[PDB]
Structure formats: C-alpha cells, structure tokens
Image (cartoon, each protein chain N blue to C red):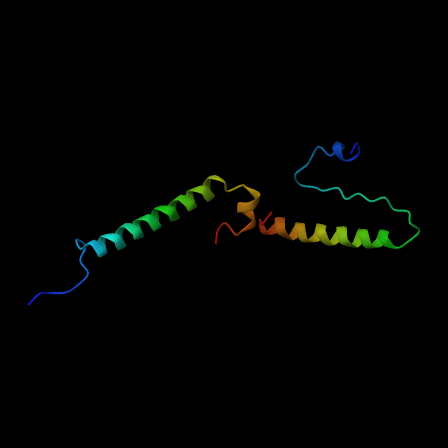
Length: 50
Length: 50
C-alpha cells in the first residue's frame, strides 16, 4: 500500500517551505530596519521593546 | 518668526505663541490647552514614546 503524507520533496511541501522561509526573511528584514532606525520618532512612537 | 528662531534647542522644548487682546477669556483657554499638551508630551518622553 502507498503511504500518504505531506513530504518535503513533494511540490506542495516545497511551496509551503519556501513561503515560510520568505516570511522569516521578511520578519528579519523588518527587525533590522527597526534596529537601524531605532532613534526615529516614528519607531520610538510604537513600543520598541514590545 | 524672529522670536521663535531664537530657540536653539529645537528638540526638547516647544514654544506656543498667541496674540492675546480680544478683551476675552481665550487667553486662559490657550494656556490650559498648551499646559495639557506639555503634560502629555512629558508623559510620552517619560515613557520613551517621543
């Protein structure tokens, strides 16, 4: 019998993996932007620690 | 403008300007509003949000 599950090699799992990696990349980019422009009044406005 | 440009410290203080007269009570209203703004901004600086 064939076994059914979402595999890392199947194209759908590949799509999900690339989307998750893209999301992590964008989150890191946003965090770096805040760390750079930490003293900016707009960045200061929103709670930077939170 | 000639009065306000004499404020070399354009970061940690603010000047609120009026023209008075009018033989009315708008002066105390302006003072009240400006004091409320000063209090709010003091709290914002104390929180770091400004």
